[PDB]
Image (cartoon, helix red, strand yellow):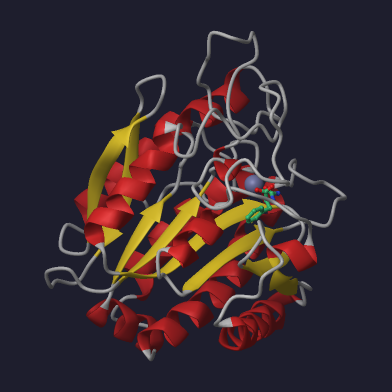
Amino acid sequence: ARSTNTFNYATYHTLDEIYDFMDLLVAQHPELVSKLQIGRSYEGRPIYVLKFSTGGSNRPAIWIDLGIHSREWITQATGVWFAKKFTENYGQNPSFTAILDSMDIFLEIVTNPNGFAFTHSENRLWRKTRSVTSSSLCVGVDANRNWDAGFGKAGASSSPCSETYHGKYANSEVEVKSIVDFVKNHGNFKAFLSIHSYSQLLLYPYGYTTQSIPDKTELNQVAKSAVAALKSLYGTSYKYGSIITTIYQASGGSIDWSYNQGIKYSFTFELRDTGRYGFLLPASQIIPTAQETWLGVLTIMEHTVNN
Ligand SMILES: NC(=O)N[C@@H](Cc1ccccc1)C(=O)O
Ligand SMILES: [Zn+2]
């Protein structure tokens, strides 16, 4: 309510509640976290990113986004928990402290604010953005089919009414371009993590082509380690591998774009579960999901620091 220590992390929140949370966190830890507005949504809502930094100019950074697909509520809920955990473990956990003393972490909890608000007021299963385009009565674009990586190719739909519609052209969605511009301007990101649900998978590039990435051997081992770490908590089983070999051919995905930009440690997490609840995961699983996911994320971060 009026203190991140009183905030209920075991329940799902609205857009306003999450945004308020950000202000409270920043007010409580001014020396560690700051709120940056990287753009505005199609409908004009501000797009915020939380920057966790210990100092420095343009220290190598880790990017983490959640909620690019509005209906995957477990992701924004995990992002809120992550934000609080960062402030609790710095100075207490030797590994994480080491990470923050040398790198910055950028966390975008609500990557698709228009769609998120829509899931709360009209359609709980909305997945796309909220932009409208003349030649169609259908609304929205699949933000994770809109990136400049094999755009328009197999793995995305060309019909505006489709849940996987890629849009008119790469980066047409302001929600996507806002991230692209910020990452490009920064120029020093070392890791790029995009979180989704559901399926319990840890994926690496590529999704748009069957071509194997040059760093396949290293990324596969990093994923193997992260999955083992995540499983150690509650025994949750995750599969891992390239997007195209694990799920299916998908074009215009964020991770493929970031990897092609030279950001080697690009991974997408697909959280719980494997279909029993799907997108409607019970609130009682928020904390356990967040706790185990953190172990997998920390593993990737550790590798990035020492590499
Ligand atoms: N559940 C869910 O959203 N799955 C992802 C799969 C994916 C991951 C990374 C790149 C491309 C595609 C989707 O965007 O459809
Ligand atoms: Zn998704």
For image coordinates 79% across by 73% down, the residue present is 237
Image coords of residue 275 (percent x, y): 85, 51
Horizontal side of residue 193 vs 98, given as left or right: right
Residue 3 visible? no
Taking 85 as reference, is 274 above or below it?
A: above
Number of numbered discs on residues: 0
Image coords of residue 85 (percent x, y): 42, 66
Horizontal side of residue 191 vs 228, given as left or right: left
Image coords of residue 104 (percent x, y): 27, 69
Residue 141 visible? yes
Taking 133 as reference, is 25 above or below it?
A: below
Taking 120 as reference, is 56 above or below it?
A: below
Image coords of residue 114 (percent x, y): 48, 26
For image coordinates 69% across by 40% down, the residue present is 156
Residue 242 is drawn in which quadrant? bottom right
For image coordinates 71% across by 24% down, the residue present is 159
User: Which of the two residues, 190 or 148, is positioned nearer the viewer here?
Assistant: 148
User: Which of the two residues, 98 or 6, is positioned nearer the viewer here?
Assistant: 98
Q: Which residue lies most toward the right here?
A: 276
User: Which of the two residues, 169 or 198, is positioned nearer the viewer here?
Assistant: 169
- On-image quarter of the N terminus: top left
For image coordinates 37% across by 47% down, the residue present is 179
- On-image quarter of the C terminus: bottom left
Horizontal side of residue 276 vs 205, given as left or right: right
